[PDB]
Every structure is written in structure tokens, then in C-alpha cells.
Length: 193
Image (tube, rainbow, N blue to C red; front, side, top):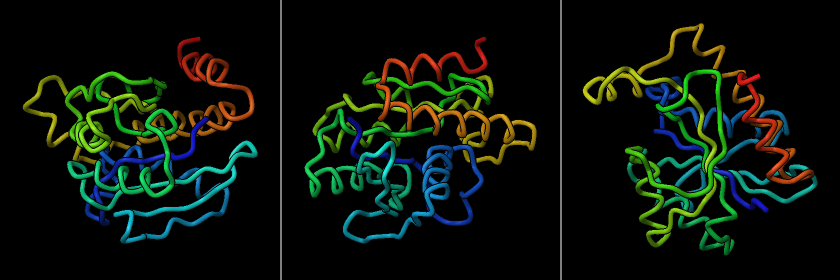
């Protein structure tokens, strides 16, 4: 089962609407719907909250370390509550999926995402945690990636990302009540059928 949900981001109003904060948008949505506000806790290097999802006790985390230093926050929370890597779900922006699509994945590398890279490192070089890949599209080549992920999406793309995040939230809840297989089958069918 999942005990911790992490949403990757950079802190501050300066980065709030940028693509690289897609993971945080997901966590914010969960907290908003449950009316369980996130509060920054120094000890965990990020915003935290505790909610009941599908009847289960789940903790939320949005690091305030800056993206490339995210591992520090995930490791601090996981160590205090004694949570295993496969009991963690990390939501993040995904260049390899278009806006409007989202997918679950267990393990694998970081694929060039520096937030994921640091988490793998800080968990003791262990990539075996779950991920919610939120599609943001790809600009074309590596040279344009920096300005793209740190850029704000046009309104039409934002609407598509919001739809995927909403569906992803419902499927995450389904994971708790009905299991990962059913939750995955529903999410991966979104926009595919």
C-alpha cells in the first residue's frame, strides 16, 4: 500500500505555475479536496499534511529544497515514519508524455529528471518507488528543455494537464480501495480510448 505521496516542485511564487511543478499541482489537488492544508515543517524540508484516502492513513509532502535537492526531504520523511521505498508514490512532470495524459510506473531510472535523480540517490541508490508521470510534452531537443520546464503552459495545455491530474487523483484513490491493477487499467485508458 502507499504511505507517502510526494509532489516535486521548486519553492516560491516565482515557480508556482511552471511545468516543473506539475507534481505539486497533484498533491495540492488532493489536499484541497480533503480540506487538509499543507504546512511547512523544517524537520522534513517541505510542506506536509496527513489525510485519509480510501480509508487509509496517508502522508503528503511537497519539498521546499529546490528540485535538485528533493531527495533530502523524501529521505527525512521516510526515515522518521519508517516508510519503505515501494510504499512511496512520487508525482512529477514527464516530458515523454503529452499534456492530457498521465501514467503510473514502478522503478526505472530518472530519465534525465534531476528531482528523481536526487531521490534515488538519497534513498540509498534505490529507484524502486512508485511514480505518477504527468505529461507536459517535449520541446524538441535538450537545448530547449530548460526554458520549457521553467515556463508556464499556455491556457489550452493547462486545461489538458488539469484534466489528467483530476483523473489521476481519482485513480490513486481507487488504488487504495480496489488495487493497483484496476487503478492502472483505468488511468492508462484515459485519452487512449
